[PDB]
Amino acid sequence: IVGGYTCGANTVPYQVSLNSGYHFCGGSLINSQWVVSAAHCYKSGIQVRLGEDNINVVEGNEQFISASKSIVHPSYNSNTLNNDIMLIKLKSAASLNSRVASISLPTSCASAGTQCLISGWGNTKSSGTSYPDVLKCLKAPILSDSSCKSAYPGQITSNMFCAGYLEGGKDSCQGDSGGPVVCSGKLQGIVSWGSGCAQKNKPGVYTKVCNYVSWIKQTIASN
Ligand SMILES: [Ca+2]
Image 1 (cartoon, rainbow, N blue to C red):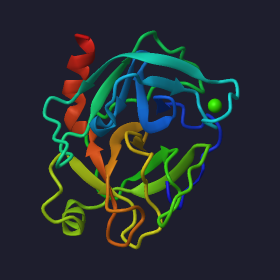
Image 2: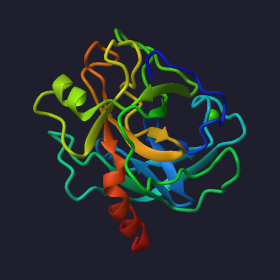
Image 3: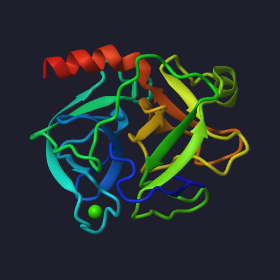
Image 4: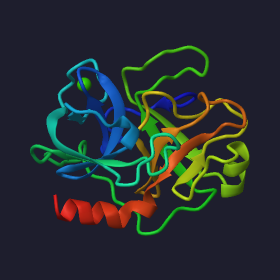
């Protein structure tokens, strides 16, 4: 997250870190057994880390639970990043309390102008590299479909939306991928892609979670 703020420990209780020996992507806990992330974060051997603030220090609220199964969206296209969503099942159910909690799925799609909370452990610099150990946060609005398409000609599908600031300086970034965009207490986006980070006229692009609620529910119901 570039141009954000330190969230505070366990203030984003649905945020998870995907770990394969190291943090590599975010995700969102949607029930005791299941995490939403980006399909482009797929790999084998995932350990889901819940209750994290500093990802390099054991602070006392963590739950580390190996994944039993990953399910990339049936229509994920890694070239275009269309349908950049996956589900990860935990080998055992997480214990839920105020610091580790699921986030609700949307019942309707959010609108341009709505304020959301984007979070992650990704790079905090737009030029060069610095990775935080504690969770960063950014409040940002959803942008119009027209301004999103004008920013990224030929690239924005109906399964994507832009959020952030066209002036630059505030955005998600590498290492945030797969993490949440939460608006009015609902998971509306997944950190997906963008041109660089926090560049002028290059806002963040997010998977549009409301399009996937029926797939998510039916997949969980049978897996
Ligand atoms: Ca920790």
